[PDB]
Amino acid sequence: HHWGYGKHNGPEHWHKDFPIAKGERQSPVDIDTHTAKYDPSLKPLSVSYDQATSLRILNNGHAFNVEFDDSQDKAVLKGGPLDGTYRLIQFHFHWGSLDGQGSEHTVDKKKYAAELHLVHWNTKYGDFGKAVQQPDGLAVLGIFLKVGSAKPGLQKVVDVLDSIKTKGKSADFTNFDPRGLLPESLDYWTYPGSLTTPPLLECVTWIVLKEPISVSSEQVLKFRKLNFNGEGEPEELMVDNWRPAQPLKNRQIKASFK
Ligand SMILES: NS(=O)(=O)c1ccc(SC[C@@H](O)C[Se]c2ccccc2)cc1
Ligand SMILES: NS(=O)(=O)c1ccc(SC[C@@H](O)C[Se]c2ccccc2)cc1
Ligand SMILES: [Zn+2]
Image 1 (cartoon, helix red, strand yellow):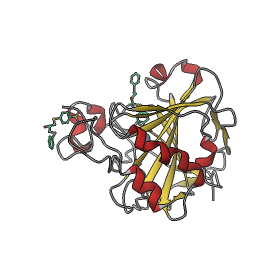
Image 2 (cartoon, rainbow, N blue to C red):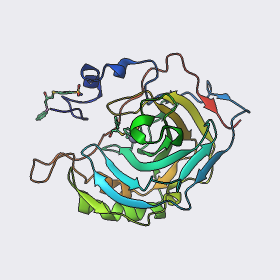
Image 3 (cartoon, rainbow, N blue to C red):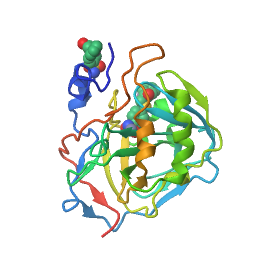
Image 4 (cartoon, protein in one colour):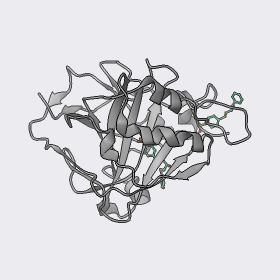
């Protein structure tokens, strides 16, 4: 058996193999917008993706990852709450079976249809596997998706999903520009947290953008045609691959904006 998002292996079970699931800085969380304090000392985010090199897209059985060449400083996140340089390694999404759920973070308990995670690692630790062992090892840029108008920059991702339907499938995915997934504003909330899947390591500076991106109903319907299963196995649609909000405990969510 293995962790997943089913009735028998979902988030309420993860603590049995990953006891840090009940830890002091777990993600995601509810963002209470009235309780978040504006921190005028936070810097604007610097998102430098013009030289991003996408390589491949992979169905890992839990989501799909768009992977980048992170062997050099090609696509980096700096500024905001961060010290130093964080290199883009991959992005992925979490989404629902219906439009009223799917995001991992919530905003005043509102769930969005989906959530994009752009995963970056702190270059002072040399590699991703070292960085996840450190409290400031990762920076994940989270962007909410709502259903409305299509996102034109998402369609190249949507159109390749039929080629990676099942767990373990990958496809070449070069020249994808992740700037096409951003909203107009880089206003954000930030707090110290964790990976939202096992192994749930407490290594993430979360940066969650206030402005959602709009995607079309047809775009998210295509995410929901993916499979958790491998080829030839009984079909289990890849939907509701989100962890619910965890206790905030002794943490403060800071806002970049008034
Ligand atoms: N999250 S975790 O790592 O602590 C973990 C590890 C192992 C397990 S046992 C899971 C199995 O009993 C049942 Se799957 C099933 C459900 C419906 C239909 C067919 C088969 C659960 C969670
Ligand atoms: N949803 S999320 O953005 O918080 C997120 C981001 C990245 C992951 S990578 C999970 C595992 O494949 C790699 Se952890 C590992 C890697 C090397 C050595 C030890 C442990 C998980 C969740
Ligand atoms: Zn994620």
